[PDB]
Image (cartoon, rainbow, N blue to C red):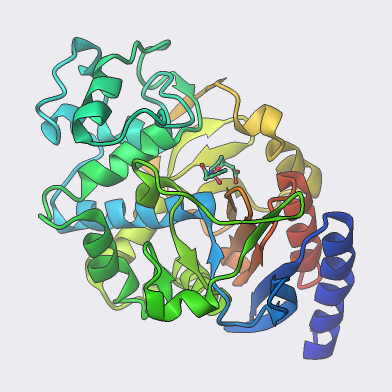
Length: 360
Ligand SMILES: *[B@@]1([O])O[C]([C]C([O])=O)[C][C][C]1[N]C(=O)[C]C1=[C][C]=[C]S1
C-alpha cells in the first residue's frame, strides 16, 4: 500500500543523510516496485565540471560485474557449451600443474578452488604470465572445502567459460547477455562518444577512475547507468519474462545455491540469504572481516535451484565508486544504489534494507 510520494520520501530521508555521513558526491538509485523502476538522483557526477547525476550517468560497478559473469557462464551451461562439473583443465589444457586435478569450473566460479587470492598479481600482464601465476599457485586447502572471495577465481571462470563460444569475453557478454536484455548503455569499454556520461569516482577528495588489469572485465570492469541497472535487476528478479531461452536458464543458474557459508549461500556471482532475514544478519555478513575471510563451506549437492524467498544481493566497489543491488523475488521488490565514492558495505546494506522494509 505504498504511494509514489511515500516511497520518494523514504528514499530521500535515507539517502540524503547517508551521502552526508559518507561524503558521497553523487548517487543514482532505482527502486523496483509494482513491476516498474522508480528513479532518484542526488548530487554530482563531476564536482569540478558541476555535472549532476542523471539517469544516464555511468558508474563503475566493481564487483557487481561478477553477476554478469555468473549469468554469462550460466548461459553457456544452458547452451551445452560448458558444465560446472568439468575440470578447469578441460578449458585450459596448458594448465598442467597437478594441483589442478580435481578442481572444477564450479570451484572457480564460487571461490572454492582452495585459496586462490583476492587479486590477480599486478605483475601478470598477459596470458603467459597468467599461466605462470596459476601454475605456481599452491592450494592451501583441498577443493570444495574453503570459500575465499577472489577475483583470481571468478575472473578465470569468466575467461574460460567463453572459450567454446569462440568469442572474446567482451563480445560474448554483449552478444549473449547485454543485447538480448536491451542493456545498450552497459560497457566493459566505454566508447569515446559515451565518455561525457562517465562520472568521476572520488577518494579522499581526489577524482579517480578504474585502471586496466588482467581479468578486469570478468571480475570488476563493467560500467552502467541506473536505468540499465534497474533493467538488469528486473531480469534477474523475474527471469520467466526473458525471451532468450538459454539466457533465462543462465539467470536461474546464477541464483542457484552451490554452497552454504554461515547464513549465506553462494551463487554464480550473486549471493543469497533466505527471506525473511533481519537487517543485522545481512549487515554483519557484509563486514570485510567476514566477507573477505577464508571460511569453511557446506556443499549444496546437487545445487538448489532459485528460491524465490531469498534476499539476493551483491556489493561492488572500485577506488572511486561504491555500489549495491538487492532484491527479493517473492515480493518483486528490489533496489539499485550507485555512488561515486566507495563507502563501507554495511552502510550500503543498512540503507537498502531500510528502503525495502518500507515496501513490506
Ligand atoms: B569487488 O567490488 O568486491 C570486493 C569489494 C566489495 O564487496 O564491493 C573486493 C573488491 C572487488 N573490486 C575490485 O577488485 C575492483 C577494485 C579496484 C580498486 C579497488 S576495488
